[PDB]
């Protein structure tokens, strides 16, 4: 028995509303780079804590600042003048005081964070040399903790909600949402990079739906070592446009789709989106945590959104992070239920109570025609109760990177 | 012009069963970053104007606050480790005298550092900017791509620097007004003079269930003005009565609970004491775009833009302009009889004049009104505002409107 609430939502689903706007910041976008680093550092520390204590100690590395470097793009080959400066911040448990054993145990927080951040950049930025193109600085607050408190956490019980916070999620994705998401995913896949190496990873996708007309506006950074002139630049744009048109036919078949790329380009004056490294982080743009995608990987002003930044937050006891991920997992499964058209899940914690015993879990369902919500309700409540029972499994999925925070 | 108007047949937020609203006050780490970011942007605007008569490309919407360390105590505590603040972003650092064939550097760094220091002096009465804070600066030169887009039609209508959207809505609900005005009052010079023990790091959350509003306030107390746990208690209760008085003025007809510093533990004397009036001194971090929207609120029950207005230039960054513009438009539409609620979403296309790919308007009508009577009045309001978009830019520079 939990405070789980099911209510029939008698509104039009977003899919059927007249207008929609969705944005996604791809992996190479500076803001998304920071989110990715922030979460990579958290996961790294999680693995660090478990490998010496078999549990996770308190930390929060949801603070990462990317300062744009200096660069000179040029057709055929560009120059990286001065490196990107990334500052790691936040806090983390570093030294454990054991009064009984009269011993101090210090953990490699700073070195782990720097390594984690560096290895993540290596993965997502193909045309960056992290040895020379990036500076990874660290000012993470390294705090202490009594080993008696470590012993209590080693029990690995369900943590108590230390705050009254909330999370929100929904499913399924609309056609527009799915198209914005998969466009970025595909343009950052190994398979496409191999066919069009000029496509950088700093990809920003904006989807506008008007009735059944979807307009995709893409900001795509081009790697200048793969285009020797404006002519080949134009060709990359049109090839990508074709590839995205092909993708739209697989997702939004039935819609009118327009695709626009780097609309601020001036082909004449050769004022175009050219980069040395494939990311505007090299000079054009700066970045930080929590001003991009939500945990479902989208920016959605026609859906509810938490302003809270999930990336880098403690997966153990941070309500916001856990509930936003949890809400989307619950909504996703409920959306698989026969008779469910759209599903919203809102979760609210009770401070002092276990995290998987919320003050209120609101399941709002838009039903398919001729379906009884009261037939769907018991199935929906079981799904929600199932995930809450397996709250620790959700925390595992986060550390293992099975779920996303941006 | 692509203005879209829709009827929205739902309960307005005022009538919905549940609501959650939040505001991070001036002294909150995140709001400090927003405020400094905007201070730097405005200072640079003034500097560029005085030097060339025109605003040059910049975006200083990037400030990182690394929390310091302090040791609060009744009667007066001590700062242990200074707060580290990093000023970042893009700016025109230099210009080229083609005739002399020589680079002329502009005073971006000194302007930015002084602006940040001046702002901190205003919002944190009890901080010592000489020892409690480090202000570093790594603002760099922007790329050649957007300084062109910035310049292509600066004398005409500026071209949008980017493809982004801003959102706005009106009117504010009772809970939203209460959260907003509570913070505004507790951070007014009027109250500070009456109760100097009130720090500026004030976080206010409003939770509504039906017609019951629970207002939860996290309020930093300045330890030099409280001799003991008893004087501390008096400040809590004094403020509590002040907010109750305010709630009677705003929340007429609602049950209003007011909880302050609920995490306090008087037994072990573990309360919200601070030396400087902000949690930043205690390791709380902050950055730009992590808190309030331009309406001054964090609202999961309302549409929001993730664009951080603070620090973005008022010339051609729609992330700033459209978020301000959307709220001005929504405000006027809400004045119309028959309109209960209005939502405005404005989408740009990078390369197009800032005056939109789509201007979206949703209206919740009064139960006995036609949208077709309202729709023409809406599109006119939206058009009039797009026509006078440059006056909005003026209001931002002049600081007649805030970005958080």
Image (cartoon, coloured by chain):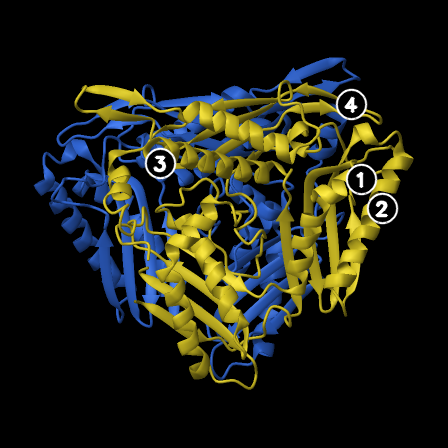
Chain colours: A blue, B yellow
Mark with earlier residue (4, 1): 4
Q: Are marks 2 and 1 on the same chain?
A: yes
Element type at marker 3? loop
- Quadrant of res B28: top right
Neighbourhood count class around disc 2 (C-alpha, 10 Å): few under 14, some 14–19, many 20 upward: few
Name the residue furthest top.
A102
Q: Is residue A53 left or right of residue A29?
A: right
Element type at marker 2? helix
Q: CA distance from mark 2 to mark 1?
A: 9 Å
Are the two marked residues, 2 and 1, in contact with CB atoms closer than 8 angstroms?
yes
Instruction: From the image, state whether disc 2 or disc 1 is nearer to you.
Output: 1
Numbered circle sitting on residue B77 = 4
Position of the N terminus of chain B by quadrant? bottom left
Mark with earlier residue (2, 4): 4
> Mark 3 = which residue?
A285
Q: How many marks?
A: 4
- Quadrant of res A30: top left
Chain hosting mark 3:
A
Numbered circle sitting on residue B238 = 2
Q: Are marks 4 and 1 on the same chain?
A: yes
Chain hosting mark 4:
B
């Amino acid at each position: 028995m939990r405070n789980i609430i099911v209510k029939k939502l008698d509104v039009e689903p977003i899919e059927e509303r007249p207008t929609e706007i969705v944005e996604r910041k791809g992996l190479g976008h500076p803001d998304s780079i920071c989110d990715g680093i922030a979460e990579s550092v958290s996961r790294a520390l999680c693995k660090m804590y478990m490998e010496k204590f078999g549990t996770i100690l308190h930390h929060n590395t949801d603070q990462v600042e990317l300062v744009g470097g200096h660069a000179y793009p040029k057709f055929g080959g560009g120059v990286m003048v001065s490196p990107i400066y990334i500052l790691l911040s936040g806090r983390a448990t570093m030294e454990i005081l054991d009064k009984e054993k009269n011993e101090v145990i210090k953990l490699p927080v700073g070195t782990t964070a720097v390594k984690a951040a560096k290895e993540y950049l290596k993965k997502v930025l193909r045309n960056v040399d992290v040895d020379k193109d990036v500076i990874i600085d660290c000012r993470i607050g390294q705090g202490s903790m009594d080993l008696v408190d470590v012993f209590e956490r080693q029990k690995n019980e369900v943590p108590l909600a230390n705050d009254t916070s909330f999370g929100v999620g929904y499913a399924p994705l609309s056609t527009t949402e799915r198209l914005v998401l998969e466009t970025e995913r595909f343009l950052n896949s190994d398979e496409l990079k191999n066919e069009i190496p000029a496509v950088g990873e700093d990809i920003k996708v904006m989807g506008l739906r008007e009735g059944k007309k979807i307009t995709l506006t893409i900001a795509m950074a081009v790697v200048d070592r793969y285009v020797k002139n404006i002519e080949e630049y134009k060709e990359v744009i049109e090839k990508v446009r074709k590839k995205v048109e092909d993708l739209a036919k697989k997702i939004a078949d039935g819609y009118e789709v327009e695709i626009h790329i780097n609309t601020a380009d001036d082909y004449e004056r050769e004022s175009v989106y050219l980069t040395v490294t494939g990311t505007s982080a090299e000079m054009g743009d700066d970045g930080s945590v929590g001003r991009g995608n939500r945990v479902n990987g989208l920016i959605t002003p026609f859906r509810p959104m938490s302003m809270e930044a999930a990336s880098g937050k403690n997966p153990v006891n941070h309500v916001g992070k856990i509930y936003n991920i949890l809400a989307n997992l619950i909504a996703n499964d409920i959306a698989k239920l026969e008779g469910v058209k759209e599903c919203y899940v809102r979760i609210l914690s009770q401070i002092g109570k276990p995290i998987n015993e919320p003050k209120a879990l609101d399941i709002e369902i838009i039903t398919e025609d001729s379906y009884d919500i009261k037939d769907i309700e018991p199935k929906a409540k079981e799904i929600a109760n199932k995930w809450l029972d397996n709250i620790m499994e959700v925390q595992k999925m986060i550390v293992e990177g099975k779920v996303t925070t941006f």
